Image 1 (spheres, one colour):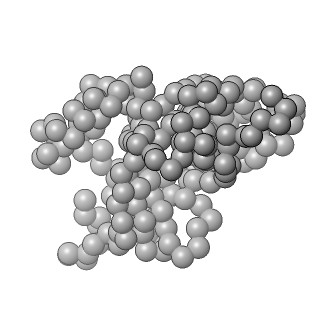
Image 2: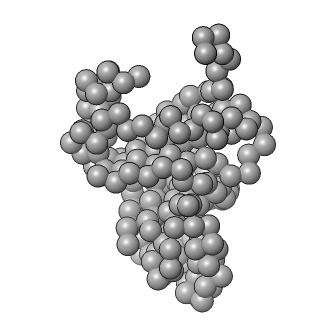
Length: 101
Length: 106
């Protein structure tokens, strides 16, 4: 039923505070039918690197795919600066149970 | 600000669905001041094992801690399809905690 997509980013240890806020940009994700929620998290107590996750909740995986194929997605997405992002991966999940007070 | 706790379960392949069923019973979590949401997920496209995550969203970490030390938690599962004594095929149960820097709900 409900679907969750995760964009897991590994950053240079300590670079989260200065890098993270950029991921708070929705960039029109809420204009996609089926989009429900978005969370941007920073993992506590990591030592090797800083870990940032962008979680998006959808009514279905089709909704998510439509987002990927949308124009708002296409539109979205100092020189020489070494990037703070070490890895960028995507994971997909079926939400088997959800409850909101 | 907002806080997310995660219980990450590695499971015998094929047991994801049954395991999520054991979590339909929130065991009074919503009675805790600060509790906001719960998500129980199954990781897609895994090969040799299953993965289920129990994510709980809170107003603060203190709220989450209050749940763990609450009477409802300390006093709170078996499925109808279980044989007496059957165990959830858990390979590992790990805990992770997160600060939620941003949240948006349509």
